[PDB]
Image (cartoon, rainbow over all chains, first blue to last red; front, side, top):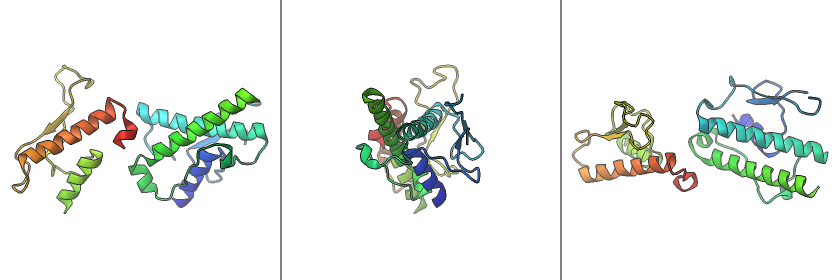
Length: 126
Length: 84
């Protein structure tokens, strides 16, 4: 799962979707003209996503990825460097530890707050 | 060794997985109509004679109360960061 943790980190830090094997839990259309549809694959999910907490967590991750991709498309940059904000996300190494601990929730909340701050700053100043 | 490991797991994360009836604290979701959605029921039960002889009943009750208060803080007070 070293590849899956790296893919999740890339999706949560830059919003870049690269799933040539249909393994990631989220993928967008246009791979209506400007607004693309983001489809979630429950067959390749990491949790059940049935309870309200898990549903809100998945929605927060998807919103973070969407905001990152929108910021990238608006700034015409291939990636969002970490110096653009005061939040730095660490890459996942142990999938079992990330699943059993709340470090996943902490990283998700941090990246979501960073994406929301960047989006608000952009839409307020530019 | 595994008994103390399960005690550690319950005292830290409030988990009772892979117990197979080898613990003295469990959850009883059965409800007779009073507080079905567990607004104030706290459906956590604690057995007495399920503990060995080398552990005090007061210490077992303290462990049960620690787990109950941790679950309460994690479920009702939403103190996610502090509980983590």
